[PDB]
Image (tube, rainbow over all chains, first blue to last red):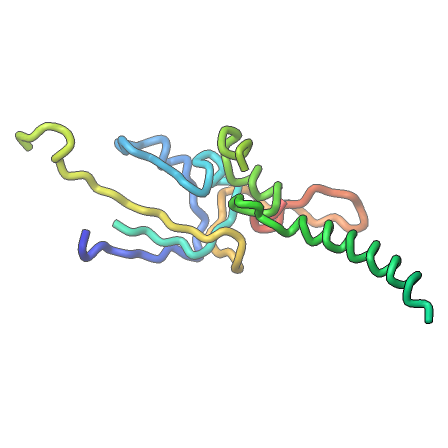
Length: 50
Length: 49
Length: 49
């Protein structure tokens, strides 16, 4: 957590449906966007912090 | 000389402009565009926005 | 592993985005349609409806 890994995601088409299809994720909480609307939107500045 | 009549015209257009300007105000919401709010959120929180 | 819930290790991944304030490079699986001119249409350009 002190040295959390940041990966930039850019120049790809993302299928979020597979995230739902296989998911042991006990917590899946979104703040600024709907989970089901992610397939219909375009984004930039995508970062994954692990 | 004709300042009074122009003033009336000046007030009316400005009022419409202010009302038009008010469409660009978030008003404490995530976005000022309704289409973005619909395209981005589920109805329980989109209703709030 | 012997501890109960609340102390077990949890992997957290935070996905961070920005909304419409820049040109977009990551998009959904939706297919692009052809362009039509001089007609009233409901368009979707990069998530802007």
